[PDB]
Image (tube, coloured by chain):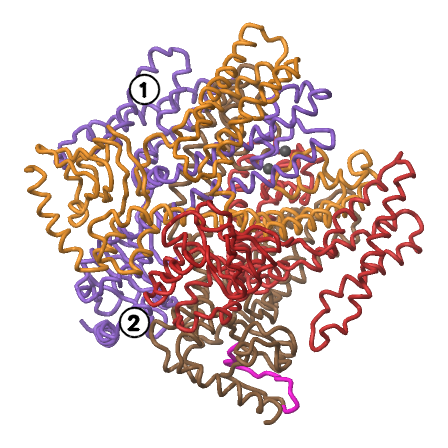
Chain colours: A red, B orange, C purple, D brown
């Protein structure tokens, strides 16, 4: 609720081309299809082939920033990005070579930041997941077995065996309900009374494990990525030790591109920002073009008013942001700091129109 | 658990008429329907047309409060509220003109406060949502493809192509289970063992993103809307800086209308309120009719007793509220404040019956 | 994880008889049923009728504790508990009179504590629920309408109207997937790609509203019910103001009945209790039978050892409880208190075997 | 996100053999199966029989550590692990004796730590669960009954009775949607509008009860298991009382086996560890092989750099771990401690290459 995320977070065309690239697949998969576009999409594969392949060698030119690096991840796919289609192109002469479009699916995961963020926490909490997965296997066959007890007599063709009932177990337990094979008697139907009761309680825990400290990591990602942009601020030499831990939980940093708007004049003053690198367009008669290490919004928060200037991104700015309460928290935290932001709420009034 | 929300939060008739207005649609959609009520409901459309249209120009009279305003939102629908039926009324001579009842659906969203509250946070956390949405697309075709590997031979008419299996993917992954096309072999049925395991883990995170800091915003909405009603209180000049951040998290403000009851006599004393504007009916022999900037309940909390008066809303009061613990927190927070609320628990005993 | 809940929390037989009472219904609902037990269960209704009716007048004897009471709730059903069967017994001469077994269903809700706990919070947060319910209605017909656009031509009998598609909306949106009427074309099937995405995000919020501050109330129920049992403790005159708010969050109170076990000897010392009313059986050669206002477990926690005595409930005791950390929190909180619990860890060593 | 869990948490072969042991069952359950492997898997049962039975007496040799123990749990299955197949082997001469493979399903639960962790909290919060379970039974028949009101006339064979509709209740309420028996009229279809609305709100609470303080217990498990490894540290005599409660919430302890890697050189310095028992391989020209009661990572955190050494597990080490923020919290918490970790960031620079 407090951030301006811009400049194409889904930026790199390495990621962009997997989506249209794999939709080329399906038309080959269909009978009675004209040969015209049949191969026209195979070009686009060759384009994406040639495109990453064009990009490939530039990546294999890893004499850029060549001091110490760990690029086993970023290279693990680019290699196979072109090899696997190639060997597929010859050995699998039939159209089945296209079935090696299971390969580009990692290219999103190549430059998927937020995917290592996922895999990080699984290596702390899987202790639970296994004991739950076991426990899921307990409840699975603990309950799947009681069905064969009953309808094997009058439903051989559906429940004349165990795994046919273990099939109906997870369908019955995992919220799904296909609707192929269902009991007819009473007591077998009684048993379902505890199943959905169970599995919704189980996954009530099990999937809960994921979001549990995943949020800790994302709420932690907002700190580790933002213990940076701390020393950059000229004013933050007085901040006590325990002060920052209270604060950086809320502070997120994002980048705005050049030409974009930052805060439009007259809209309700609801937030203030800290500039640390870039330049702005504080839209005034004399534009107060503030550079790395600046801020604005106290004019609108101490007064609780609309904006005093159509601030727009003159350049690509690495932005911070902050809503009132946590700044009211700061204004409540120390009288030493409100002195400057009092003067600032008088300097910027005259300094906005003037120079 | 601690608030008296009253006076028709779903107040404006601009919102009320969308619901019955769109139920006029369906009777036109049905064969063998008598022409009698067929057009009778078209009137009610013309009523809602004429009604907002009657309301319309009063809104286009925006010389009220005309200093600085941002009403691109509130006007964006009122314009089309009447135009779109109108052009639809003539060009689409057949009854299909009624199909432009997709238009009023924004009129709730016109005066839907809590809808901008939604859209505010999506512009901070969609970074995650995309990486998850990509990741959802990863897992989609990563898993959808393995089905065509198998049953294309003996299920052409169901799994003789890829998207027919991507169809069975999300139905299998997104908790649904329609039950149209399901495997027959073993290993294809083995694969589902991880799917519901996956998607319930995925949406365990993904929908978790929404409620994650959505609650922060709603728990924040309870502050930004209630840093107001702070200076109004005559007693709150002594409150230290860090005191309020502890408190305003819990304090919610709502309005009660005239004639309503506030706290009924003899019910268990469970809460105390702060009046800031309006008037009450403290039901006593001499009604102690307290106005803007008053409170009551300490009589019932310091003693832990039922109510001392059938307080009812003499007028429309902008109410605050507070349960014991957070006031016990206040009574624990400072001895300076319990002095007055000790006297108040003696003044109001005699002042209730007397003047 | 830290409490001994015993003495039949589902105690009153007023609640017990609704369950078997309503299972008497179904046998009447079935053809080809013998008249033998057909009316035998009607007796059990007459029993439950006569039983509450026997209990009834004792409740209508409300000259017990007749000072100030609010028993509109507890009486609202007992009245109709016997009247509604009675008027049903005569006017509805056919067996349909049994269909007034929709009446006892409130008798659980009569003496359902935890049900007012539910209804308390709905009167603070329904503001959200309506805006979401509206928003649910937005997304409902916003999406339901686009289906009639498509398959009305080739599916009249299923999608030849709007509400037939609004039917398929919530089934498609609310996680269910019956499997009666599903599209055949492409773009109509494309639309489902966002639906489960939506509704699982919606209910990801909407049902989240319930548990959101419901837990606040239950975590609050653990305080309001336990600001009692505070002054009872002879030692708690020194506890500072802000000390208790830290503590009572964790402290739960429950009752154990006479004859039950409290802590068995040799089991791992994992918790300590505060007796406030009742008596125990500290199983020793000289049983140190401690009465109202006592405690035990510091012997096992300061040493981190198994139990020093098979403490069992000599009588019905109103119990408190506490795990180590929060007592380690107390031992960390003040050196003034560990002095006594040091002596206590020496007195009770000799006082256990001796008197 | 901050722990190295290794050395086969799913270690004991007592647990390993239940999974393959029960998959021996199904082949017997199937007609037209050759007798060759039919009994070959019965051997593997006899193996698992003989295997635990071989393990059995070693467990019944409970003169190891025979001082005070509570092994009613660990023995409750081992006894029946071999007896139940045995009596089954003779009395049930037909192949049905295999149906006593419902017995090993507890053997995972025998040595399932994290299963008592489950059962611990159910004995505090089931108060809620019953009132919800009752309330679930309220809503069940409250809603199930209204269906028989309607379609009994034109759907006898599906809704000609009550429990046939209570069947359609939970299927309709518990998120499932089999798709066997669905209404045809309007008002009966209207009723579903509140059902999924309800049950998703109910289980929104009910399953929420599980994860609610289950996480408290797991977040508590991280303390009770880690108030140990406190006195072992030679430096922690100065830590104030309230300091540790802040810290041990995050600190998890796990064990790494011999031969494994701990932190690889050049990877981004993201965490520091506390050795308390074992030995390491700090890969340097002179390996600084640190033993019980050591730490490392401050070199990479105070500088925010990659690793200074390929530390690998020379032996099985009982590890602790800690990310920066909580150590930055420590560095912010006291200047007394950064003095040593300043010297340590100079000693270990020279002491790494040297001795
Ligand atoms: K379903
Ligand atoms: K289905």
Q: Quadrant of the N terminus of chain B?
A: top left
The residue singled out by tag 1 in the image is C84
Dot 1: chain letter: C
Hey, which quadrant is residue A62 in on the image? bottom right
Left or right of B101: which side holds D338?
A: left
Camera-side residue: B48 or D134? B48
Q: Are marks 1 and 2 on the same chain?
A: yes
Camera-side residue: C233 or A7? A7
A316 drawn magenta: no
The residue singled out by tag 2 in the image is C331
Mark nearer the N terminus (1 vs 2): 1
Dot 2: chain letter: C
Residue numbers of the magenta segment: D273-286
- The Cα–Cα distance between marks 1 and 2, rounded to whole angstroms, is 60 Å
Q: Name the residue at 89% across, 58% down.
A: A87
- Asked whether residue A264 is in view, the answer is yes
Hey, which quadrant is residue A253 in on the image? bottom right
Left or right of D241: which side holds D276?
A: right
Hey, which quadrant is residue D86 in on the image? bottom right
Circle 1/circle 2 CB separation < 8 Å: no
- For disc 1, the neighbor class at 10 Å (few under 14, some 14 to 19, many from 20) is some
D277 drawn magenta: yes
Q: Quadrant of the C terminus of chain B?
A: top left
Q: Name the residue at 19% across, 67% down.
A: C238
Left or right of D248: which side holds A97?
A: right
- Asked whether residue C350 is in view, the answer is no
């Amino acid at each position: 609720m407090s951030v301006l995320p811009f400049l194409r977070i889904y930026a790199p065309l390495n990621a962009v081309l997997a989506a249209p690239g794999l939709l080329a697949v399906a038309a080959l998969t269909i009978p009675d299809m004209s040969g015209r576009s049949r191969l026209a999409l195979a070009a686009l594969l060759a384009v994406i082939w040639g495109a990453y392949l064009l990009q490939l060698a530039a990546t294999l030119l890893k004499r850029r920033a060549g001091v110490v690096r760990d690029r086993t991840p970023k290279i693990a796919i680019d290699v196979l990005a072109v090899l696997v289609p190639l060997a597929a192109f010859l050995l699998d002469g039939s159209p089945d070579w296209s079935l090696y479009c299971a390969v580009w699916l990692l290219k999103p995961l190549r430059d998927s930041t937020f995917f290592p963020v996922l895999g990080r926490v699984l290596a702390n909490e899987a202790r639970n997941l296994i004991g739950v997965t076991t426990l899921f296997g307990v409840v699975l066959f603990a309950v799947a077995l009681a069905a064969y007890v009953i309808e094997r007599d009058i439903q051989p063709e559906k429940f004349g065996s165990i795994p046919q009932a273990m099939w109906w177990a997870v369908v019955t337990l995992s919220t799904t309900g296909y609707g192929d094979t269902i009991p007819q008697s009473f007591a077998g139907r009684v048993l379902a009374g505890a199943v959905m009761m169970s599995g919704i309680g189980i996954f009530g825990l099990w999937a809960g494990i994921l979001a549990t400290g995943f949020y800790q990591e994302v709420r932690r990602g907002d700190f580790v990525r933002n213990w940076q942009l701390v020393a950059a601020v000229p004013l933050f030499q007085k901040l006590g030790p325990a002060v920052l831990v209270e604060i950086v939980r809320a502070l997120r940093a994002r980048t705005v591109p050049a030409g974009a708007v930052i805060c439009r004049i007259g809209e309700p003053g609801d937030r203030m920002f800290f500039v640390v690198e870039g330049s702005v367009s504080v839209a005034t008669p004399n534009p107060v073009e503030l550079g790395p290490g600046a801020f604005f919004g106290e004019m609108a928060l101490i007064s609780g008013e609309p904006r005093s200037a159509t601030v727009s991104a003159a350049t690509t700015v690495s932005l911070l942001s902050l809503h009132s309460a946590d700044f009211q928290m700061l204004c409540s935290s120390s009288p030493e700091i409100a002195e400057i932001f009092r003067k600032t709420a008088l300097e910027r009034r005259g300094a906005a129109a003037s120079a």
